[PDB]
Amino acid sequence: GPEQREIPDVSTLTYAEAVKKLTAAGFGRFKQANSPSTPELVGKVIGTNPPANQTSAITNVVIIIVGSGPATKDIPDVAGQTVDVAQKNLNVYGFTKFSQASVDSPRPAGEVTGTNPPAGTTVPVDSVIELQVSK
C-alpha cells in the first residue's frame, strides 16, 4: 500500500461528505477556503487541491474549497418615505446594516432621497447600505 491515499469523490456532493470520507481515508490535515460561486451549489466542495482521482501522501495538507453562495440583494427604491420607515421596509427584504448620509434638503426633509449605490445594484446582504437622507 502506498503512503498516498485516494481522495473520495463524495466531496463534490457535500462538504460534510468530503470531510467524513476523507477523515475515514486517514487524512487529518486540512486547509479550508470558500469562494463565492453559483448559489445552487452552496455547501458542496467545488474543488480540492489533492485530486480525487490521484493518490496524495497523507502528510499533505488538503486544501478544500467550498462553494459559497452568498445572500445578495439589489437595493430597492424606497426613497420618498421617512428614514425610519424606509429602513424598516428595506430591512425586511434586504439589509440590516445601515449608514446615513446627509444630503441637502430642498423640498423633502427627513425622508430618504435615495441610496448610496444606484438602485438595482446587487450587493451582499452582509454589506453595509448607505441611505441618503435629506438632512
Image: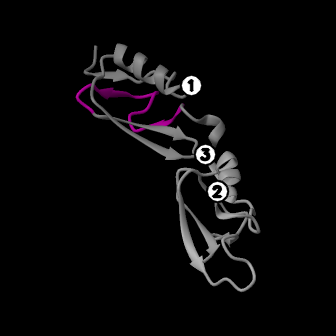
Q: Which residues, given as a range, are shown in magenta?
A: 44-60
Residue bearing mark 1: 13
- Hey, what amino acid is under mark 3? Ala
Closer to viewer: mark 3 or mark 2: 2
Give the CA distance from mark 3 to mark 1. 21 Å
Residue bearing mark 2: 87
Mark 3: which secondary structure?
A: loop
Instruction: Name the residue furthest left.
Output: 59
Q: Earlier in the sequence, mark 3 or mark 2?
A: 3
The verdict on residue 51 being magenta is: yes
Give the CA distance from mark 3 to mark 2. 18 Å
The verdict on residue 57 being magenta is: yes
Crowdedness near tag 2: few (<14), some (14–19) or many (≥20) residues, C-alpha within 10 Å: many
Residue bearing mark 3: 71
- Residue 120 is situated, as x and y percent measured from the top left of the image, at 73, 63
- Residue 5 is situated, as x and y percent measured from the top left of the image, at 33, 21
Q: Nearer the viewer, residue 6 or 88?
A: 88
Disc 3 + disc 2, Cβ < 8 Å: no
Crowdedness near tag 3: few (<14), some (14–19) or many (≥20) residues, C-alpha within 10 Å: few
Q: Quadrant of the C terminus?
A: bottom right
**Residue 3 circle label:** none
Disc 2 + disc 1, Cβ < 8 Å: no
Residue drawn at (63%, 44%) of the image: 38
Mark 2: which secondary structure?
A: helix
Total marks in image:
3
